[PDB]
Image (tube, rainbow, N blue to C red):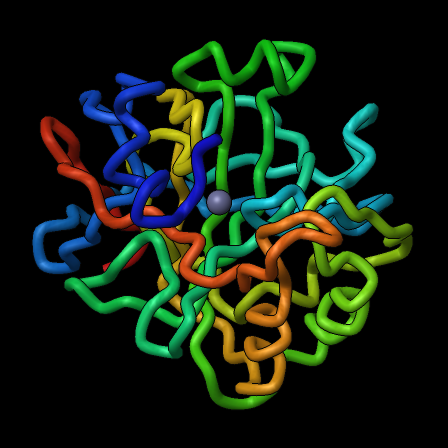
Length: 257
Ligand SMILES: [Zn+2]
């Protein structure tokens, strides 16, 4: 029912999902001057060498690249986190135009897209239990700007023709998510929420400062996807981003000076 249109978009979500107006909603604007450097924060540990990608799915709101999360194969630890978080999927948010698409903003700057690598806290046993907990998820967010191509993204781009419409999936084995990371792991962190319904307040957000560059041709392929199912009126999958929400009683911390 929910989506990104005039009639079912982010300004309507609160009617079915009242937590939409809650105290720890995401995304937010990152005001770089008021974020506090926190010397007690640790380097992030991204351990993706044994990652096992399985499948790519058009779910009607984005496409998800799904992983085997039945063992500790691709995990996030350190940084602001206690314990071990397993990678379950990644997906993107993007615009109809290069001047919009990201969910987080930086001093009100919107990027062309934003990658979310979604991980759940192994102490809760599965994703569905983790989303019911205030420290259940850790989401690594990475900005995309348009410039040079990202070679590690092209295998994703090239499979999108096979999953044009809602409900389509394709085999997507042997994909290495290390090829989507920038050089630096410097980050901001704050407590927040899922950015799609059910909007649960279960996320430790870790947003990298350094964007990756992708080509205009790469992002143009994202914008050829469809929100609709096969045989239905074509609606391009663009502008699948929630705008910045009120920060309320939260502090954004920086890992770097
Ligand atoms: Zn997302």
